[PDB]
Image (cartoon, coloured by chain):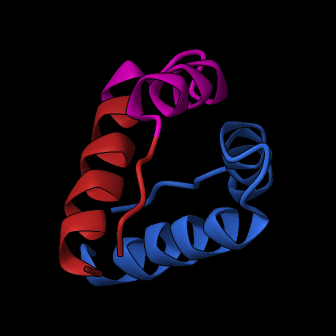
Chain colours: A blue, B red
Amino acid sequence: QELTVPWDDIEALLKNNFENDQAAVRQVMERLQKGWSLAK
Amino acid sequence: QELTVPWDDIEALLKNNFENDQAAVRQVMERLQKGWSLAK
C-alpha cells in the first residue's frame, strides 16, 4: 500500500494523550511504526 | 505492553491528513490497528 502516515503529528497526539508517560508515547509510537512495517 | 491508542483521534488526524482520500484514511487506520495487533 502506498500510504504515508504523519508520525510527527501522531507523536504529538500520543504525547498529549500520554501527558505524563512520555515513555508510553515512545512505546506506542514505536509499536505503531513497527506494526505499520509488519502489516504491510 | 499495556498501552492504549486513541484510534478516534488518530482517525481524525488521518482524516485531515487525507483531506481527499477517505479510502486512504481507512487503509492507514486499519493498517495501524492491524500492525498494532501484530507488533504486540
Q: Residue at x 27, y 53 (%)?
A: B33
Q: How many marks?
A: 0
Quadrant of res A23: bottom right
Residue occupying image coordinates x 62% and y 66%: A24
The percent coordinates of residue A2 (x first, y second) are 43, 60
Q: Relative to B18, does residue A4 appear above or below in the rendering?
A: below
Q: Residue A7 falls in which quadrant of the image?
A: bottom right
Q: Nearer the viewer, residue A31 or A18?
A: A18
The answer to whether A29 is drawn above or below residue A4 in the figure is below
Segment tinted magenta in the rendering = B6-23
The residue nearer to you, when weighing B13 against B19, is B13
Q: Is residue B16 found inside the magenta-colored segment of the image?
A: yes
A7 sits to left or right of B33: right
Quadrant for the N terminus of chain B, please. bottom left
Q: Residue B4: image x %, image y %? A: 41, 49
Q: Eyeballing the image, is B22 above or below B4?
A: above
For the stretch drawn in magenta, what is the main secondary structure? helix
Residue drawn at x 44%, y 46% is B5
- Residue B19 place in picture, x, y as percent: 60, 16
Q: Is residue B22 magenta?
A: yes
- Residue found 45% across the figure and 24% down from its top: B21
Residue B37 in picture, x, y percent from top left: 19, 67
Q: Quadrant of the C terminus of chain B?
A: bottom left
